[PDB]
Length: 279
Length: 279
Image: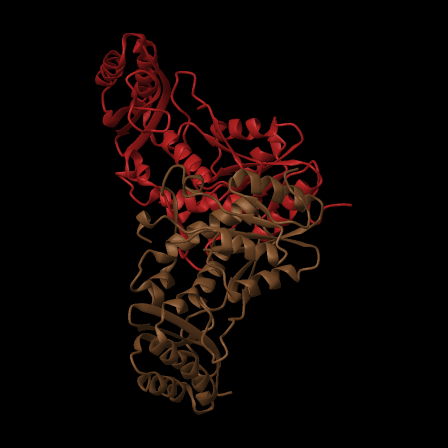
């Protein structure tokens, strides 16, 4: 029994939700485990790590969606697909805005209060757009696991709330941030940094790593070390530098947490975060 | 495991009914879901019977009411007795804590239709409904879900939910069951004193009169309904509207729906009927 419209071993591209849903359901029925990697295209090494994390799950078929979601606000379709082909990805889902929101923004997802904080201050409706599209992609593909990068930590935490709050039957996998050789978190925004800004941008990761090691001396020491590193960089306007628990609530007196930073270099906004252990 | 065929199996933990439902689906039995708030009457038994009619089906009837503190009183014992007597194999009766372990955090935001008609006096009512229904659909993963046509707006909003979030379930509307005189069955009817019960017949009489007046056009149909309601002692009408079957504007001719909501004392009653204009 062949699967309608699906060719094992090759990059199969689908634009209609119904097509990828049928293919995914037939594949699940034969016992394959469907992995979903949601992206907005313009792929770089960061995304490829997500793809590889998905691919290495035994008996898996990897679905990578490319969809620049209007609701949560780079375009090289062929470069993107070509890169996915090279990774051995078998399915690419590339729907049009029309096929995803045929009735505009009608029924949508309202995130909890965490969505109004940190990234949500500068962009109050951003996460509603992200959870709405992620929920839709989860229902279309019905994957066993969905992969997101830790770079957008708040996003990852909000997706975990989505999945828990709506009893979604999918495991959420956070993948460690892929970095450049000097530590700069990979991001499509890095290309907008001019030479001096690129050099100065190293301060974000350096400040966080300094903080994580300074942490044996406590929270004030960790924060102060990060700040000193940021104070030594020119042109890095810090929007926030916050210590929180892993779910982004208040940081406990001790234990595990996450240190997050967001800064603007010229008009380019950069983010980074790192696991922290107090004391 | 944990499921005895031919008997009423009662589960409180989401994980338990999800496992059982998953297992029953594997063996080919299609899962039917009938969501209710308890206080079952003949109207609900009609949903159950329509679900039972599906060839190889196992019927899941859930009983749950959102916690009042959300801003959007009985024992489950008689309802279960009823389900058992009706040959239902699964009852899902979760606690508020098990449905909302992290409280009301991520929720569903309905489209504009939720602010109209029933949504006027209760702005967040449908958000609560769609949120719970979405969760029940994810927990039970049924092939079909049944809702009564009595709550027509609700039914329409549930169909938007399923389409907008790409849910893979068929939504079945079941015709309203009525008392001998035409009164739509509802657990609220028991709150009508004798005079109110007698006056309450005006809702269905007004709708049926309109459906037949319709050969003379929509305005004539609305006028007939209004005249009947105006002749009814102590019936205070909240709204009486003729719309499209999707609840959009009613066209020149074609199918539609006439909806009415009224107050008799402090008991609010609803009813609606299919209308064929210029036919």
